[PDB]
Amino acid sequence: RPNLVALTRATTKLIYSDIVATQRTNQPVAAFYGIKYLNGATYAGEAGYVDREQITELTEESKLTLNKGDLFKYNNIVYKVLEDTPFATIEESDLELALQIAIVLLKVRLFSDAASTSKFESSDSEIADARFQINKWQTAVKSRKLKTGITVELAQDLEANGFDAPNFLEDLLATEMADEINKDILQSLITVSKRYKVTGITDSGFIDLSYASAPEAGRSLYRMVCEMVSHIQKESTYTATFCVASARAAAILAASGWLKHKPEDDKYLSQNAYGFLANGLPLYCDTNSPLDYVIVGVVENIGEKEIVGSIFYAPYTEFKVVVDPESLQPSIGLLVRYALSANPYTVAKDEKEARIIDGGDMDKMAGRSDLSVLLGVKLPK
Amino acid sequence: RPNLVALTRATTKLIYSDIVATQRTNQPVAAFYGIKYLNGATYAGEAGYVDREQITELTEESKLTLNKGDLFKYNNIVYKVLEDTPFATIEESDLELALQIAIVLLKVRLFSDAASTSKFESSDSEIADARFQINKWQTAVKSRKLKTGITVELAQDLEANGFDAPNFLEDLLATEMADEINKDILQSLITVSKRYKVTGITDSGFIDLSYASAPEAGRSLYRMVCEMVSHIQKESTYTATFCVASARAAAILAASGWLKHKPEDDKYLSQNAYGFLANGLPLYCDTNSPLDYVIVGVVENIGEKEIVGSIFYAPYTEFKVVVDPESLQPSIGLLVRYALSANPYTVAKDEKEARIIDGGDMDKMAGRSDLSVLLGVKLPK
Amino acid sequence: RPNLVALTRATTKLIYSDIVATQRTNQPVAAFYGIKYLNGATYAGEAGYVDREQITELTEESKLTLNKGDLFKYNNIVYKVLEDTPFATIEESDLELALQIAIVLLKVRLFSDAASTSKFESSDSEIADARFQINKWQTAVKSRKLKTGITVELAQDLEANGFDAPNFLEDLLATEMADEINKDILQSLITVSKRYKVTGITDSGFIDLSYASAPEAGRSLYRMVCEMVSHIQKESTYTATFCVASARAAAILAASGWLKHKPEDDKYLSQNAYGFLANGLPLYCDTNSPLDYVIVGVVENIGEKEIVGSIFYAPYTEFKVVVDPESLQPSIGLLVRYALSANPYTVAKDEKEARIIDGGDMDKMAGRSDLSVLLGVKLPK
Amino acid sequence: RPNLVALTRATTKLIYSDIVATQRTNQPVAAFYGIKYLNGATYAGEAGYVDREQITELTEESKLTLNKGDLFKYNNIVYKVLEDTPFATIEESDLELALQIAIVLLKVRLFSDAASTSKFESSDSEIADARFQINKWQTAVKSRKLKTGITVELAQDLEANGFDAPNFLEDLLATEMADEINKDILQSLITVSKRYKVTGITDSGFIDLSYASAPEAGRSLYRMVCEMVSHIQKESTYTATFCVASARAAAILAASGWLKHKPEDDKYLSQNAYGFLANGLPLYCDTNSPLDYVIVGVVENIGEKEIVGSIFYAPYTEFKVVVDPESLQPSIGLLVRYALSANPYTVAKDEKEARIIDGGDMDKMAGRSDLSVLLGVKLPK
Amino acid sequence: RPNLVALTRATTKLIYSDIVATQRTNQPVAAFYGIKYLNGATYAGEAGYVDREQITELTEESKLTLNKGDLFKYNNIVYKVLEDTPFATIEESDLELALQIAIVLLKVRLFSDAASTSKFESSDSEIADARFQINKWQTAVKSRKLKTGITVELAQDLEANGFDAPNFLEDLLATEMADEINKDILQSLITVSKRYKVTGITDSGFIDLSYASAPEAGRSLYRMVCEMVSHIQKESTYTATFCVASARAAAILAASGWLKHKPEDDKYLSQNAYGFLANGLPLYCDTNSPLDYVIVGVVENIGEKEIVGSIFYAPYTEFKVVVDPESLQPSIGLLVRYALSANPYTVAKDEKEARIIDGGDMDKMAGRSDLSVLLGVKLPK
């Protein structure tokens, strides 16, 4: 239906299609797709996995009983021993650091399992496993309808303003619809995003830049936000692609040199974006959420497929506007339906749990994104 | 009259046509239009409103009588309860903040009323109402005449300078006309803009960067200006789109790194702009008002119609420049007429009050923009 | 004279042609034109002025006798009274500031005299007078001449360098001529520029960044310069369009982050600019004058005519090169002539005084630009 | 195999192909080439060497026995003596500095052995030998393989997603493969890079920005990273061309104004870069290595050949994807083979050592890049 | 010889051809040309000079005996007296400053000798002499040669690498030649550059930012460097055009915020630039000299001729490559020759001194550039 296609074009141009992954449906449900994995470094191969288990866990009671040429693993990373008794000269008790140090000082070597053709073919060894699994799920399409284009005495007013009024009123209707869609998206993103936490939540409490705390410059938030990106980079094979925040949270707070105020509007910045940060990521401004929060996350793709995201959006078209001639008031209404969801497998161990949940159930998906993190923020007022 | 079209273009190119919404008339009055809503969050339907009233106002006393699956609303925002007794572990006494905490801690979830198509069609439920409505009003077209192109002995001098004088003089005269028009607009904007206020005005009194206060860098003003932009975003679905300030207020004061000196003018900047801010918005400069103030506000549109602004401008053409040869002086007279107004519905409960007021009456519209805010500023004088 | 025109093109490109206004002559004297007004706001009509006279001067003893609906004026700006006894609640003793407060708090309202067409036509009301007058004056075309293209054995040297020498030497001679001309321009500009003075000269003495004062970063000068631009905006209907400073004054001194070294050489920047500032304005540098000063001011045009400026330049062609074999030496003489002047009306009440003065008499025009100011600067030699 | 050519070209776009030198093979081994010299100043000729030997080693007891016209050399730099007894007036006891002082004070002069041909031909002298030698080596092509494109019930899922599933799965597998390859490269770069060290390592211990040290802004890291670039400039004939770091180490840590977030994805930056430093060089973000390190180094070419690099990559093509219908699971296997190596010459004096080592042996090449340096960083964890 | 043409054009792209003036020869010596002179303000005319002498030297004893209309001179600048007894109200005892002040306060006026046609023709007056004097000198073309193309066993390696080897080798050898040429130039620039000196050398000693002084940020060096530009501007009719410094002296030091690492290079920078400074002129880097210095200076041209430079370069061709296949060694030689020089007249009063010296004699030209200065720097090593 070309008229719905046109209304769709004129309404979705106004929504945050870029802070969610976009897919589409033609079904009562949307068949959504996504990619996930629970651990990250080196290989995912089983042959190699077994070797890791068959070499050593690197217990601190064994770290120095190793000698030149030996292998060991730690947190699944295989390393070779350079010269004898690695760590003999390292006072550090924490293996995470003792190892960090040992690598730097060339006591141990990050081990590469690239190997000859013969290794594989002769051994008839296992082969590397998947880094990620690809999921699919079906989430019902939900809708909302507006009945707002009031006509009657208004029809006369609209006729008086008839130059623009026919389409104008439909466009105004679409505008409010887009706004409600964006709110719905943001609520889901807020809900699904993992809470960002460091040492008992962002340096042992939600970041607090309140009057009684640290009304500095806004710099300490910018630092925390930058760290949120590192978290994503640490935990997933991506880099944050977008950020959303309220004005008080960052879209204004970061104005103190930590925010790039849309110097250009067609370069790495969408039309609905507020701007981007001093460290990039198009920044979107929420403006509605009472939290004055910040979200950092990833929306990505495989070829043309927007399969990577915390939230996925899939409109169901075959954005319809109608007039209902009730009484003397033949007003204009607008119906929009879409599926909105998170990858349900991030709350499931396997398909026998995924099959009894719904990616659109934001009570269950709460805090389970892993492609996004949420910063709670306390501000002056 | 094509010659007036040419004079119009050669005069309006010189005024801040974008710091007001621009409409046009052909009537003795301009039929102005604009959009307003009296409150945000979620859907605007009666069904919603009823469900909200039918669940709870979240009286603090009742916050722990809530359990998993329950709904509640606060400040008209609907939330669902995640697990039992939300807020049981939140020591915060200010319910607004306790709620923000509950959301980030996933004790409660921002709730969407989206539902299946069947829900609505089967139940014959109500439908979301309009949030914003379009208002109309009529404001008289006022005018200003100049008798400034003096010729006589002056004609002789103009003849001596006859190389340029004919058109030169008309453009010069047009320039003075444009100046007065622009200034007239700015005075209206100053008057209509809401006074910016936080905790008893800009942090309990207007910003004071005087000698006895904080002759810092001007950073503290930028901060407040940025908050003004936030305020607009908080209270309306717009970001600031422009700002005007005097030199001492910001057009010079902010030139300590928070003002961009028109690096370029063929992109992202109107030709009469002084430059733009570090907060992106086109910075204009008045230079006349004794106030040395800063105004932040928004102009916008639905498709082609500039329906959003604190002040609306509507010139009436059918920029008349004629010779008035009284005595021995074939001098040039210039007449421009236009309507200029604020949306009168911002000072009315309904149309029965709007119909007895005038959007052009700045004694009534004063401080009632909602699409702009004014910052009073005390300087090192 | 095409050969001289070619030299003109190749020589005037080497001077700061845009820090002064450019006009041209074809006469032994140059007829210069320019625009001035002596006090900026609202209408300049007699009706306006009379109504202002008929309402009040807003004296301290009368500001409280005003009530709702009354008008008053101050510093020629008309304001309307909002509600009774404006200023009743304002303790501020400086009436001008009290007024600024009253505007912000909506005790008074910036008032526009714009009115219906009928008001004007019915009463046969007066009309706005001109704000600015257009002046004309003439000065002699003055000249300089060189005997510097030395030839003899030099001819032999030039013959040795004969692949380039004919043109090379004329271009070189033209260059040194251009250099002195540029310097001459600066002397006139320096002289005419008004001394920037605030509270007994730029915060009660010329800015001093010497060792015994403020050997800081140069920031305090950058701030003062930006304020010089404000001064221009205050006193004239223009923003600064250029700035020139010595190395020690600002071309180097402000190069601590508030000065840019021509990052781009073809956009909004002349080929002769040293660079531009962080507060805009192409930046020029004199390098000769003992003053070590900074000048801020404006060149502006109506169509093609550079009518606005502190100094006006008007070259006279019909760059003459003459080859004269004194004895054994066919040296090259170079002659360049132009008018250069300040608008004499800045030192005159009317034509009777203008007719007995000379815009080229810099002993009278000194400090009388109003379209430019100079900052004296004490430096940490 | 055109399909593999396409898969390779369309997949290697995802690895840090430019932070290594890229060469290619068609053999079971890759023939790699690279360039090295042991010292940088003046000519590398025997005649020069002898003249230097014949004048002095600049013993501090002899530094002042020199007089005007004499030559001396120090650290292979030849200097001529200006005036008598150079250093007579230099109190500095450290000859390295005393020389720097003498040079700046014009007591000595940097000397060139350039001369007329007559000098050379008459003398029948020697000529400069090569500074840099070109070394070649062969390193076996190694591989990694996936058997992860799972099909069965998954085939049904892929059919359900049949719209684009065939290529999707291959593209995804190729992506995961690219990721593993890139990891292998990074481990090799980490290993080969020399440990940056000043006065016992980065000012007597690895940079430490831990909470017990200097949790500043990240400024101090930027400084050390920048110093690593100076090291590259000092010890080679190239400037750094790239930088790679973990997120915590710098992609995020330096995003306090010392790092740019890829504001442009096609200007002095590859598509795989996270950004570029405030001081340039595309910055790649590792994200996997536990080291939290920073690497600065070079890749450079002569004509089309990327002859210079610490690590060299040489893929062996004739990204192979096949399906193996074992059981009911006809999964997609993917194999990629390439040589990866360091120039073995950096750990050898000559061919009799080079012939018993392998550029691909990272247990020997560790710390021996000379075209890269790594900074260990202790972070505020 | 087309092969010399191709090799030279394709290789000199690698030397700092723009930090010297480029000229060319075809002779065994190069005929270099250049401009120097004694001062920089107003005219160079003898009659005007005499007038200066005929008015006053402005000794303080006479500064108060001057009255309205009088002229006086100081440091060859003529100034006019405004009103009587100039300086009567100036407490300053140092005439240099008293004059600076008097000019600012309009007690005196910079005097322009632009004059009427009558002045000149009536008196049949003299005419201005040259501000500049033009020199020519002849400097021998010296050669530098390489026997760097080692082939034998290497020839077989080159055959193995026959894909690239023929030209690869010549290009590489040519690259090393470019390096030596560049280094040769830099040594000459270092030597000729005048020591930047202020109050006994850059604030009474070479700038010292060492740990024993001021290990700040590097800001103080940037300030000194910017002053070096000032020096060029004060001493000559040019601004600095380029800057070269060691890696530690500026390429890295200024990374702290006063250096941009080539964010753009298809505009305003040479391909061999490191980047450019915050008060930028392309920043180049030597990487060899132990001095860790900074050079600031200027090259300039009249049409196509680079008549200005501290050092001039003039190559002589008829990059020549030869082969000497003794035994099994068909090795490649590379020969390049050029003249390199400073304007010898900077160390001569007249031709009887210039004719017995050589601009290529860096023992005599040491410290006598005047078109460049060098700063010694003590770094925090």
Image: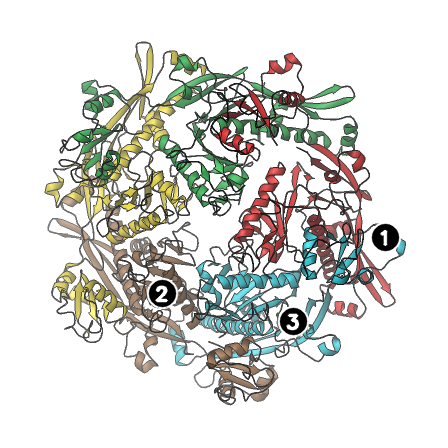
Chain colours: A yellow, B green, C red, D brown, E cyan
Which one is in front, A99 or B189?
A: B189
Amino acid beneath label 3: Thr
Q: What secondary structure is found at the residue carrying circle 2?
A: loop
CA gap, disc 3 and disc 2: 41 Å
Check if mark 2's residue and mark 1's residue have beta carbons within 8 Å: no
The quarter of the rendered structure image containing the N terminus of chain A is top left
Which one is in front, B262 or D122?
A: B262
Say which quarter of the image contains residue A172. top left
CA gap, disc 3 and disc 1: 47 Å
Question: Disc 3 or 1, which lies upstream in sequence?
Answer: 3
Nearest-to-viewer mark from 2 and 1: 1
Q: Are marks 3 and 1 on the same chain?
A: yes
Q: Which residue is mark 3?
A: E25
Q: Which residue is mark 2?
A: D23
Amino acid beneath label 2: Gln
Q: Residue at x 13, y 33 (%)?
A: B67
What subunit carries mark 1?
E
- The answer to whether one can see residue A114 in this image is no
- The answer to whether one can see residue C302 in this image is yes
Q: What secondary structure is found at the residue carrying circle 1?
A: helix
Residue C142 at x, y percent in the picture: 80, 49
Residue farthest toward the front in the current orientation of the protein = C61
Q: Which residue is mark 1?
A: E119
Amino acid beneath label 1: Lys
Q: What secondary structure is found at the residue carrying circle 3?
A: loop
What subunit carries mark 3?
E
- D379 shown above or below D199: above
- Density class for disc 3 (Cα within 10 Å; few <14, some 14-19, many ≥20) is some
Say which quarter of the image contains residue A59. bottom left
**How many numbered marks are there?**
3
- E253 shown above or below C352: below
